[PDB]
Length: 68
Length: 67
Image (cartoon, rainbow over all chains, first blue to last red; front, side, top):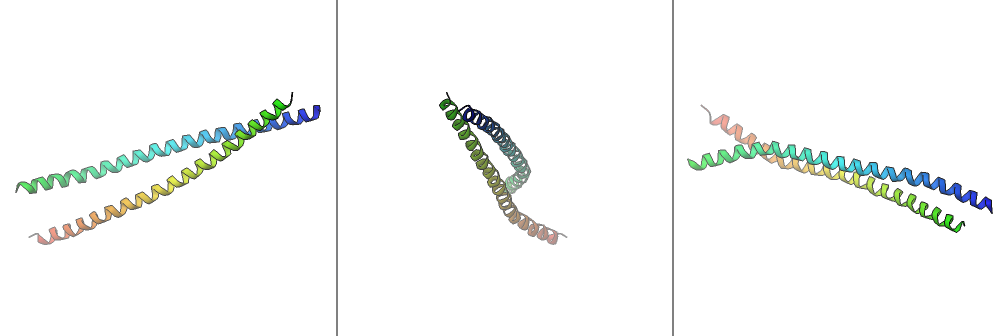
């Protein structure tokens, strides 16, 4: 009977180990995802800047053309 | 008592499984993102191409109308 107990306890310690391990894996991945979203957003913002200049030059060309 | 210990073991087992499944979901999500990004960048490239071509034609025309 004490054997059953000892074995169950062993099992429990094992699963505590794995449970913890994967619990941290999740955390890491969540962090990684958040980083990727941040970085992605930043790069899109840079693209938007790059496009803005074109848009303005065309705007001013257009209105300037619309005066003459 | 050891029924308590059985229950606790099974709760832990539940959690280990749960976390493994969550990891697989998240890895999936990451891959899908890496796909979607790629695709969208390519779409942007296509959309820029047209403007590029029109500008090229324009620049030729402007150079040629010169005196």
